[PDB]
Length: 40
Length: 10
Image (cartoon, rainbow over all chains, first blue to last red; front, side, top):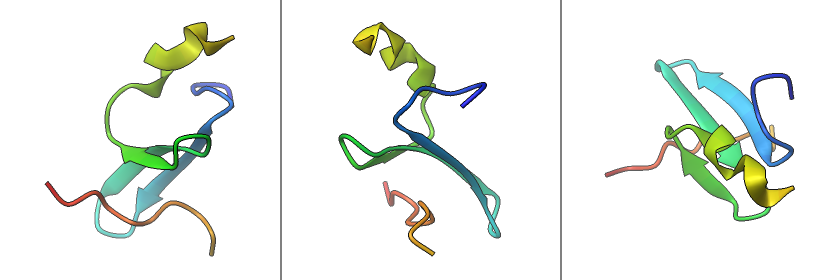
């Protein structure tokens, strides 16, 4: 996506939780995923 | 859905 790498699904949850979750590692993280960008 | 809603519990 625009913010966010090709791993990712930005879901801000009905509790107040935007989990930036990677689909290649299946990791739910609140840490900046764009950090992984060098993956390309 | 199959969207990431599973909050990591620390």
